[PDB]
Structures are given as structure tokens and as C-alpha cells.
Amino acid sequence: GPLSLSVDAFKILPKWEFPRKNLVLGKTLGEGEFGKVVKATAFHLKGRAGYTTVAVKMLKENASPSELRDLLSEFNVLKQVNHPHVIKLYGACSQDGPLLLIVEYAKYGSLRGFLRESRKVRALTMGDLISFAWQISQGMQYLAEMKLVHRDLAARNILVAEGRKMKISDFGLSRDVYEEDSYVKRSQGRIPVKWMAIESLFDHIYTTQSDVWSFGVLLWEIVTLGGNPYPGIPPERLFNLLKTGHRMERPDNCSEEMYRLMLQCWKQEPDKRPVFADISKDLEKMMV
Amino acid sequence: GPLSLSVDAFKILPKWEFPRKNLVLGKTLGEGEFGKVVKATAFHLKGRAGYTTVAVKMLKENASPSELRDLLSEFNVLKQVNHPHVIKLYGACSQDGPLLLIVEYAKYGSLRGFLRESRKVRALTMGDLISFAWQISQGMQYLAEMKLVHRDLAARNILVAEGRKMKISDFGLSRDVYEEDSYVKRSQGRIPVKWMAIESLFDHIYTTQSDVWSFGVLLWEIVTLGGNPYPGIPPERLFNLLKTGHRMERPDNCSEEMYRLMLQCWKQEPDKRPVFADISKDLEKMMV
Ligand SMILES: COc1ccc(/C=C2\C(=O)Nc3ccc(N)cc32)cc1
Ligand SMILES: COc1ccc(/C=C2\C(=O)Nc3ccc(N)cc32)cc1
């Protein structure tokens, strides 16, 4: 099938390969959907003398064809992508054991955990908050320019690297949209309902503009310091609440220009939402 | 889409509804893929005076359209099914809060945990082991007769109820095959690679005979007291090992007639595998 074809083409296929003997695995940093990520260290990694501390993405126990598919796809995507606000790939190990992707280690963990262990003024201004949002916007403008739809943009999918630098990660669900400017999935998707654009939920259509919708949910998360979207509202209720025109209220400690920006990422019509370029301009304005 | 249609038809739709006020939730029993299961107690449940201790299946945090789809489907399936070796449904709560399915509580937990906390002779004969396998076979013959393909048969998906009684659970991935005797999924499935039949892996075809293959993996698990299939072999290696005719070796403390039975559930050609009726006969033979 499509998968066995990919796996065999992959096993037959550069400068992405890394000796498994030079990689040492350590504690688990995170799990969840699709994979496991462990802290690691790599000896003589792409020109760097000695050890570099890295993160290693692998298949969890009992992986389905779907999670294997997502791992190989994330690898194919990350090889093409380069940007200061996108996670960096160093290589992979595929030869004498499990498939492992060697990626950039982020000193501060996920954006969601980073926010949750902090407070509004770890102390963080709303100027830091908006700075976070902005770095992500630039990241996203870049991937949009690459004709790439992330699909799974969320605080748990952004890493905080050294310097409090945002890195977009988790390219498992990302899809190329060069040809048609849309990705359409016939079956039910694996993105959390509460982050999906209204057209993705009802019609299974994903574009840069539905990434825009997720970005609005992610702003909400940033502003709330790691709150849970639509708190206390079950996911199945979202179909009707969204189509009947309902949206999350302005949270506490949110400025009107920020909430105004979220509201615009959640317009029903994908065309009436801003594009990442104009989002970034909006945030840079707010940040002064 | 197909999902919003189901959700609205469900919200518009008997004697399956249960007052949410009469249900009390308690500790988490299990999680993983698709849902969470919590211990609960239900007041005045389907004719039963007082409280009955039950299990409650719900959506985990941040559920995708896919997990919601699997929850509603499991509910639709469980309403049609009745057998001493299939989990019993009591009802659901859908009205004023999250969707919850109220099912049979199994005193001993999953078959996998039950086996792992035991020893060959908690002490268990190989006669108990084979008894477990047999109860599952009868369960499966019944669902096969209902023209139902389980798809996700595995020790973690069997519960051990009072009397050490096996109950097949987790009907999330189950599919009706009345019309065509097969279920075909175009996209990549969410069943663990190591439990899927060779035709399911390569061609995305599921039938009662690929359930037979999973049952062979499950026998292996029973015999090994909760071992991990294909230990130390990465899932992606399975395509080639399976198509080149490789199979798990006879494990320790396994009789030849038992291993002979697994080997037959793993024939390349779905037609050369036994049917559950003949599997059950084989096990009842062994059990003396
Ligand atoms: C201070 O605690 C930490 C917690 C999580 C991380 C996680 C990741 C990390 O460092 N790089 C990653 C790449 C992909 C994914 N999914 C996760 C990570 C790092 C540090
Ligand atoms: C002694 O420890 C226990 C551990 C898990 C259970 C789990 C379930 C249970 O009791 N009923 C269930 C129905 C569906 C699923 N997935 C799981 C369960 C019960 C008892």
C-alpha cells in the first residue's frame, strides 16, 4: 500500500544518516499522539566536535501504520524546512534498529508547559507573551510561503528554545499544498477538535487560512498562560456552537486589540481571516 | 461531513439514556488510544435497585474528530451485541455534559495486566491459559456470525471479569461487513502494526480472517503471560519479515499443538486460516 511503498523506498534511500553508535538516549521528555521524544546526546553530529545534546523522536510502543506514516512524513518535511522559528533536523537513524529522528533540543520544553509554570506581570510581561506569538507568526509565514499547511498548531506543539526562542514542531500532520492550495482528508482527522477551523471540522478542508484559525486558538492559549480552549464545553458541542457563530469570550488580562486579532482568525470565511504577514505586523504594533 | 451528520442525528435521537445525576465517576482505570475509562457507580441502573459499580468510557482531553467518531461507533456497535464473552453496555449519558458510555466493570482489569501480574504453574495452569483463549474464541465466533470485524483484538482489549470470565471490549475500530464480507480502509489504520494481518498491512483489507490473525497474536500473548509480540523488532520491519514468510518462533512453555494453532492463524492466505468455530474446537481438545 502507500505505506509499504514508503518504507521500502526509505530503506533503499544521504547526509541525513547518523551512526546509531554515536547516539545516546536518555529520559523521556514527552509523549502523546504519534510519537515519543527522549533527551539524547550525539557524538560528532554534523561537524560539531564532541557531544551535542539533542532530542530524539521515535515510535511509541505498539505503533499503528498511521503513526509510522506520520513519523516518515515529519522526516520528509523537516529535511526541506529551515527557519529560526522552526525546529531543526540533524538526521535520523534507520539502519540497525528502530527509526529515530534526531532533532533540536529545546531547553525550556513545550510552550504549554512553559506558560503553565509561569505568571503574568516565572514572571512574564504581556510584552513577552506577544513576542512569543510574533515569533510563531514569522515561523508560520515562512511555512505558508513554502506552501506547507502545519494542521496541528497549538501551544503543546511549540517549543521554547534558548533565549526564550519559539520553535514550531510536530510536522507529523503537515501537508504539501503547492498544487491546489488545500489539503483535503476524506476520513476523520487526528487534530484535536478544539483547534480545528470550522471548514476543517465540517468539510475536511485544510489551508493556510485554517492554520490561521489554529493560530487564533494558540493566541488564546498564550494570553491565558496555558488555559484549555472552550473550557468545560465538550468537543462534540463544537460543531453546533461554531456553525451558529459562537466563539470564545475575551479572556482575562487580554487587551482588546489582541482579542480582536483572535476574533479575526476565527472568521467563518477563510478569506476574511488575516494572513500570517498581517498577523505579524499586528503583533509588532501591539508589542510597543 | 460524515461526523457532523452523526453527531446531530445522535443529539436528536431510547432506553439507552441514563440520568447524568445518577452516575458517579471515580478513579481512572485506563487510557491509551481513542478514550479514557473510569470506575463509576450508577444509581438505579436498568432495573437494578441501589448502586451498581460500572465502567465509564469517555473522550480523553483534546479529542480529535477521529476519537469522537470511534466513541459513537463503539456505542452503535455495543447496542446490537449481546454475549457472555462480549462487554455489556448499560447506557450512555449525552444530554448535559460530555458523552459517556456506561459499560460493564471487570473486577480483574485487562487480560494483559492480569497475565503480567501472574506466573505459570498469581498462579495459573496452562489449562487456565487455554480456557482464556477459548472464551475469546466463542466471543469471536459470535461477532463473526453478526458479520462484525473487531479489527483490534489483543490482550489489552480483553477484560477479565468475575469468575475469570473473558469479555471482548473496545469496539471503537469494529466495522460491519454484512454486504461485502470485508472492510477496506483507504487511509492508514490505527491498529498496532504488530497485530495486523499481512493483507491488512499491505492492502488495507479487514475480514473475519484477519481477526483470526490477531487472535493468533493474542494466543501468543496468553501463552507468554503478556509478552510483547515480535520482541525487539521495530514495527516498520514487519512488512518485509511478514511478506518474506517470517513468523514468531515457538515461545517457551508453549505446547506444539498451541504453536501449531498460532502458525495457522498466520497463514499468508486468509482462506487457509481456521475459522473461530474450528479454533474453539481445537482449544477444547487441548484443554484435556
Ligand atoms: C525542559 O523540559 C523539556 C521538556 C520537553 C522537551 C521536548 C522537546 C525537545 O527538546 N525537542 C523536541 C522536539 C519535538 C518534540 N515533540 C518535543 C521536543 C524539551 C525540554
Ligand atoms: C482491577 O483493575 C481494573 C483495571 C482496568 C479495568 C478496565 C475496564 C473495565 O472494568 N471495563 C472496561 C471497559 C472498557 C475498557 N476499555 C476498560 C474497562 C477494570 C479493572
Image: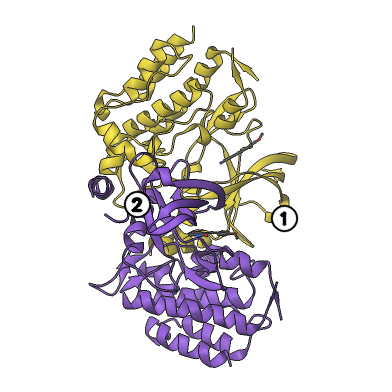
Chain colours: A purple, B yellow
What amino acid is labelled 2 in the image?
A: Arg
Which element carries disc 2, helix, strand or loop? helix
- Residue in the picture at 48% in, 56% down: A54
Residue B275 horizontal side relative to residue A62, left or right: left
Q: Quadrant of the C terminus of chain A?
A: bottom right
Res A246 visible: no
A272 lies left or right of B47:
left
- Tell which of A162 and B68 is nearer to you: A162
Label 1 – label 2 distance at C-alpha:
43 Å
Residue labelled with disc 2: A69
Q: Is B275 above or below relative to A265?
A: above
Query: Ligand 2: which quarter?
Result: top right
Residue B173 point in image, percent of width and height: 43, 45
Quadrant assignment, res A188: bottom left
Q: Give neighbour class at mark 1: few <14, some 14-19, many 20+ (Cα, 10 Å).
A: few
Three-letter residue code for mark 1: Lys
Of marks 1 and 2, the one in the foreground: 2
Residue at point 42%, 82% (across, down): A276
Does A259 sit left or right of A264 as displayed?
A: right
For residue B225, above or below residue A216 = above
**Badge 2: how crowded within 10 Å, few (<14), some, or many (20+)?**
many
Q: Residue at x 55, y 88 (%)?
A: A260
Say above or below: A108 vs A43. Answer: below
